[PDB]
Image 1 (cartoon, rainbow, N blue to C red):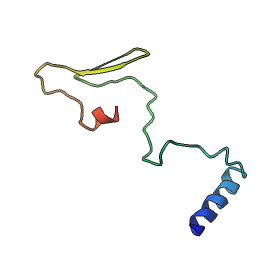
Image 2 (image 1 turned 90 degrees about the vertical axis):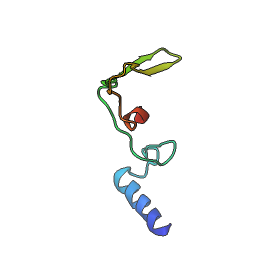
Image 3 (image 1 turned 135 degrees about the horizontal axis):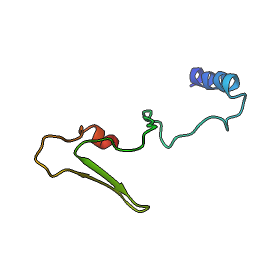
Image 4 (image 1 turned 180 degrees about the vertical axis):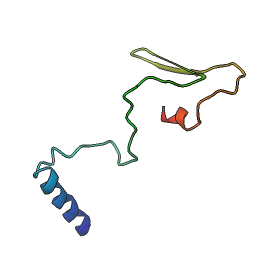
Length: 76
């Protein structure tokens, strides 16, 4: 703890000038998230709609073998 806290202190004082208000805050300490200057789904076999109440994703019922990564589909 000691070693880490000297680090966060050293680090605050050296890049936040004491102001812990400057230290950004997240819900839980998890993995960084990817920013898209797009924000629009350029994804095949997937359609994307939304209101103020609901976001709709649905995948083409066409038998064609074009669908999103199981990975991508969950990042979304």
